[PDB]
Amino acid sequence: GKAGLELRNFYFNRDYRQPSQSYSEEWAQGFLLRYESGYTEGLFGLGVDALGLLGVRLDSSPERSYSTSDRRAAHDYSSLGLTAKLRVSHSTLKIGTLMPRLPVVQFNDTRLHPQTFQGGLLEVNEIDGLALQFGQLRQVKQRDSTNAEDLGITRGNKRNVSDRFDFAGGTYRWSERLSSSYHYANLEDFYRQHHLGVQHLLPLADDQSLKSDIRWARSTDEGRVNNRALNALFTYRLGGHAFGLGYQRMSGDSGFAYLAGTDPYLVNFVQIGDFANKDERSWQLRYDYDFAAIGLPGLTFMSRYLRGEHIDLLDGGGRGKEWERDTDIAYLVGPLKNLGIKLRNGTFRSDFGNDIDETRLIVSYALPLW
C-alpha cells in the first residue's frame, strides 16, 4: 500500500530559428498522484496501480517568416490510469497503464506529466541474476496530451523515416557489476529492432571507478527503415567529479528507430538533439560535479558538448554537422524538505538548418502519502 503525490512547476522556453524565427514559452503546474497497491496472498496475488494526473499549462508562441503569427493557449487536464497486477512468486503481469524503462521503449518524463502507454507487461525474474520482460503496447498518451493516439515512429528531420508494439528481452547480471542485455522490439508494419547492451563498472581506487556502457542496435523494415546504431559512453568517476567521453555512429539507410515521443536509448541523446540522423557520427564530452564532496549535498552541475557530423542530407548532396551544449544545475533538499529545483540549458546549432536555444526551470516537490 504505497502512495504519494508530486507537485510540479515547469517553465520552459524555446527560441527556434532557421536562417524564419519562432519563440515558444510554457508555464505549467501539475499534480501527480500515484497509488501502488499490494498483492492478495496466495500462490497468485492480485494488485492494482492507479495513476492520477491533474494540471494546467499556458502556452505562447509567436512566429515570423513574409508571415507573422502570435498565439496563446491554456489547457487543463485530469486523468486516472489503472493498471491491474498479477504476481506468481517472483514474476509479474501488468495490464492497463504502463511506463516502461527498456532499451527498445523508454517512456519520456521531462515536461508536465509522464508519457504513458496502454498494453501489457510480463516481468519474470525466476532465475537468480536474470530479468526478462515481455509485452506488447497498443497505445500511447504523449506528455502533452491526455488523449491516447496510435503508436508511431520518430520521423522527419534527417532520420529519414499501428496499434501493436511487441517486445521481448532481458538482462543477465554476470557479476554484481557486469550486466549484459539483449532486447527485441517489433512495431507492426514498421520496424523490427534488435538491441545488445553491456554495462561494466570497474572500481579502481576506493573512491574512483570507470563505467563502460557499450550499446549496439539494429532496425530493419517490415512494410522502410534500415539502421545500425553503435554507441558507447565511458565515464571515469573520481570523487565528486565525473568525466565522460561518448561516441555514437549511425549507419544504414535511415537514422535511429524509436516510438515517437519516447527517449531513444542512445548515449548522445541529450537535451535538444538525438544525434541520430542518417550516417551521423557524434562525439560527447561530459563533466559532472556533485557538491556532496565540498559539503553541500544535493547540488549538482553538468555540462556536455556534443558534435555530430557526416550527416547525410539526402537532398543537397553535401553533409551536415551540428553541435550542442547543455548545462544543468540542480538543487534537491536530507530534511526538512524534498523540494527539488532544476535548471536546464540547451544550445544547439547546425549548418543545414535549425538553431535552437532552450531553457527549462523545474520546481518539484514529492511527498509520500504515508
Image (cartoon, rainbow, N blue to C red):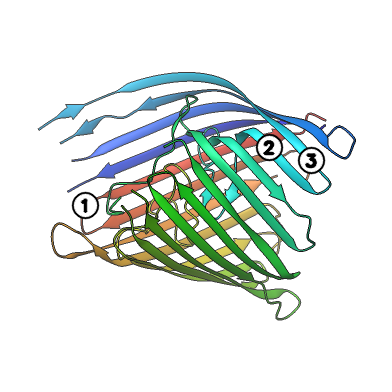
264 sits to left or right of 136:
left
Residue at image mark 3 = 87
Residue depicted at x 49% and y 34%: 140
* CA gap, disc 1 and disc 2: 44 Å
Q: Earlier in the sequence, mark 3 or mark 2?
A: 3
Q: Nearer the viewer, mark 1 or mark 2?
A: 2
Between 191 and 112, the one lying in front of the other is 191
Q: Nearer the viewer, residue 184 or 216?
A: 184
Image position, residue 213 (x, y; %): 57, 69
Which of 342/190 is in front?
190
**Quadrant (top left/top right/bottom left/bottom right) for the C terminus:** top right
Q: Residue at x 71, y 54 (%)?
A: 297
Kindly identify which residue carries mark 2: 94
Q: Which residue is mark 1?
A: 353
Check if mark 3's residue and mark 2's residue have beta carbons within 8 Å: no
108 with respect to 253 (left or right): right
Which quadrant holds the N terminus?
Answer: top right
Q: Amino acid at mark 1?
A: Gly
Mark 3 surroundings within 10 Å by alpha-carbon count, few (fewer than 14), some (14 through 19), many (20 or more)? many
Q: Secondary structure at mark 2?
A: strand
- Decide if residue 339 is in sight here: yes
